[PDB]
Amino acid sequence: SVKIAPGAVVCVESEIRGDVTIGPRTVIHPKARIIAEAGPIVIGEGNLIEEQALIINAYPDNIKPMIIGTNNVFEVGCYSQAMKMGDNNVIESKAYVGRNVILTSGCIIGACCNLNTFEVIPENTVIYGADCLRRVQTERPQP
Amino acid sequence: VKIAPGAVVCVESEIRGDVTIGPRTVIHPKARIIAEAGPIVIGEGNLIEEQALIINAYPDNIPKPMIIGTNNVFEVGCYSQAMKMGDNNVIESKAYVGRNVILTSGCIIGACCNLNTFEVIPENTVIYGADCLRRVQTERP
Image (cartoon, rainbow over all chains, first blue to last red; front, side, top):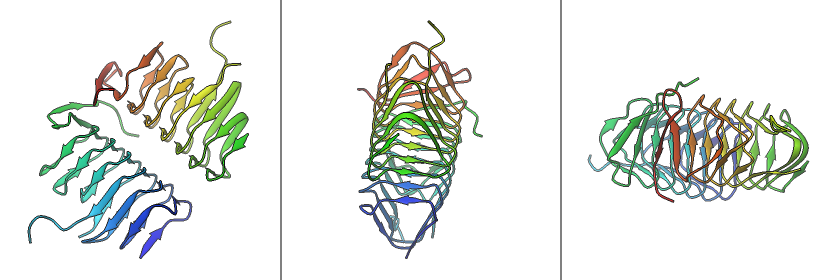
């Protein structure tokens, strides 16, 4: 069953299936898909999931919960299987974040980037290029 | 203050003056939207987070409207005077964006940055760096 915090804004035209928990201040646009397939999904306070974004707790390519922190922006048509994500991240339009990727905090995944890697992204990283071959440090604080 | 059907304006928010709010836009508690020197027009699907400040102010010099597009994000505590913004821009927590800064689409202003220049930021630009002087384009317009 789907559990939304009072004061979260989830549009009727979004697709939300499985054991999903939505923190307060979170907003989910129409046509966003959130699917707790292989395990629960937990979304924290103050995230934005935009149109056609796809978030899925999927079975891997081999034989539990997906945890998302606070203040992350999932831009239109992006696709995430990352099982853990911290705070203050932005995933840009049509970027893909793979199941073996762990996002920390303050990161930016560039538009159209296909990040299907096995790694923990250091804090404050920007990864961009369709290829995902470029990385810089934001050097910004967090608060 | 004109609010479109399907927009969500939280009760503890502050909206003053000639402000138009498009459908699906969400305005959180303690956000401030002030149309002081001119109107503010805000499009669809924007998100204005707690304690964000958006103001159409008189310039620091001696009524033109502020125009904001679709799916832009004003994170907690940020402060914007930009008079024109397109689509899919993210202004990160506690950043400042100036009156003569024009954002196109797909931009990200790094947390706590102070961006008070005279220019049109190219699409898909990330403002970052220790002094917020570094820029990169994640993708071409």
